[PDB]
Length: 93
Length: 93
Image (cartoon, rainbow over all chains, first blue to last red):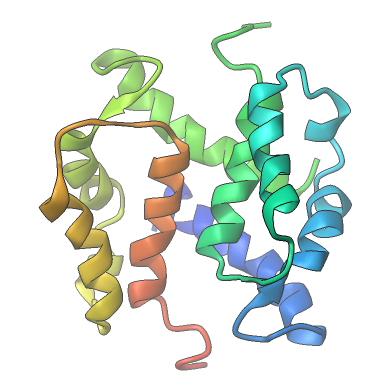
């Protein structure tokens, strides 16, 4: 349909990727969320210019890293650390 | 970097699209969230097989549609109505 519609289709593509092999199928554990982030990313964490935003995403694990995600919680987090590093308005070129 | 990394780069592409012209620049109003959804989508709402999930996303507007989003709240919602219609495990072909 559009670049936006397929945008979400790309997120689930990686989700069901591991959830299919080993996981809760319908959902995924938070333990993997750690590696799953870097394992797939491994670029946004190579900066982390900010700290307040980086603390929030990290604070989540500090609170309770025992549970399971539900896509919505996995897609939202992916955007969390994104802004923490990503420099759009902060810097142009 | 990867299909996942660019995945988020596609979401912001549409965000700054309107926010740039008319909006809060740093953020966007919720009033547009309505049309912004269909205007861009116009496919997931052509089904809405579920109701409980469709009620949540809609309930948000029922509560208070007066405010501004912050990407994280715009990307998470985009995935909300997605699962409401999207039929992955529910149906294969």
